[PDB]
Amino acid sequence: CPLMVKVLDAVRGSPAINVAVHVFRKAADDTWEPFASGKTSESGELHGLTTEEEFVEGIYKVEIDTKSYWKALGISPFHEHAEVVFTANDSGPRRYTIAALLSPYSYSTTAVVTNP
Amino acid sequence: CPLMVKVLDAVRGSPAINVAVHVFRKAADDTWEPFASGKTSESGELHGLTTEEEFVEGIYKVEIDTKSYWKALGISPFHEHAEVVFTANDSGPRRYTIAALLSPYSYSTTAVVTN
Amino acid sequence: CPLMVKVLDAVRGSPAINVAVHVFRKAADDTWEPFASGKTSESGELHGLTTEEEFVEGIYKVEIDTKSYWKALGISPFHEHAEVVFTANDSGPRRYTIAALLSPYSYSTTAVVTN
Amino acid sequence: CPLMVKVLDAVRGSPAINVAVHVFRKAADDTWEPFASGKTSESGELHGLTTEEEFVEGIYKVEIDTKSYWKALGISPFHEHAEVVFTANDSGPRRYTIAALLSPYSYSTTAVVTNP
Ligand SMILES: COc1cc(C(=O)c2ccc(C)cc2)cc([N+](=O)[O-])c1O
Ligand SMILES: COc1cc(C(=O)c2ccc(C)cc2)cc([N+](=O)[O-])c1O
Image (cartoon, rainbow over all chains, first blue to last red; front, side, top):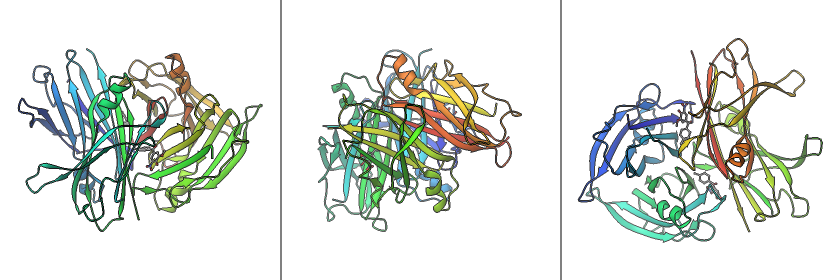
């Protein structure tokens, strides 16, 4: 599993469950092509987005649907979504965890990149 | 000044100076229309982006060119840029500060919205 | 003003107003000696804590009374308080801003140190 | 394992390995009594600090030795250590993960609290 997304809720001190995530990859014509999508589990984690074969070098955008998350909980937040945009696999295959910590008016994101 | 952007460097403990910032407004066709731009000052702040007259309700994107900032310091960063996407609302308070705190493999953003 | 403390609320997107802040200096016997204190203003800022003459090199602790802040808002928080412990150094730049960004179960802190 | 500590490095995009952690508990006389200590593993995690029986209700301080971490890597950081101070188990036993994200002049900490 070369791309994993983990989301935490800083208000409740819990995993952020059922957060929708959409991943895009920049195509040859410079548009954002849909690449993979899913939702976080009870642990706040989203596994199984892609495969080693499919996750080639490119520029990827991970869009974490934070507004949809807060509004499903009945809260009006500030951001539409969090966007994490990065070049992947340009020195060979790596494993990427994109972690996000959410509050209604703030979020932080970090990447943990490992070499198998 | 209804919109201000402030950028900070978590590695050196300093304002992030001379960082390019581009603001876009979402158009009716869902594309991003250039709206305003500038570079952060010696304080890490970018003032004067827009006016109350121009800054109507809608969805805006603030793009912060973090990659060039880190590379000009000789540091290899993870992200292409940082993006902050939000709705401007007239029911809320009138002044928006979008603050960003930068590290090579991480960034955070908060909104401080006041009258 | 060699030391300023700024506190922000990540839940409401606002300055954190009327937050108690206590600063201590580490004494020769390793205890914490009261040094300065105050409450954040309407801007979330606390100015005037000390002077260049009083703020000598050494280890300081800034304690931010986050628990009372959240409870006054009717919110149950995780931490007793936030603590920031650091060394003041004359080799560095002269002005220290300790900024804190608060959520009920999380907080972050950065130092912005400038001339 | 009712108390776990996880530390990440925001400069390198990696777990923060070999970070020393000291846990204290406020005693009846209001002093900080040493409670447990350890160091983060190759995954950035520290398991095995305490037991369900030993981890009674109280006020705990988790001291993450961030300066020692950065100085062992040859970097001069701003903070002496990160301190996370919280009441535990006052509504019955819970499981606590204290997560920290480190940069030389900044850190963030979050708690993930679950009910077995
Ligand atoms: C990256 O892995 C994790 C991160 C965190 C964080 O709290 C967090 C902090 C800052 C950011 C930006 C993101 C995550 C907590 C858990 N955990 O409870 O297992 C993790 O596994
Ligand atoms: C030095 O002056 C400021 C510092 C910062 C921060 O350090 C901050 C932390 C987390 C984040 C995400 C952003 C910035 C914030 C504001 N501000 O918001 O007004 C300041 O005016």
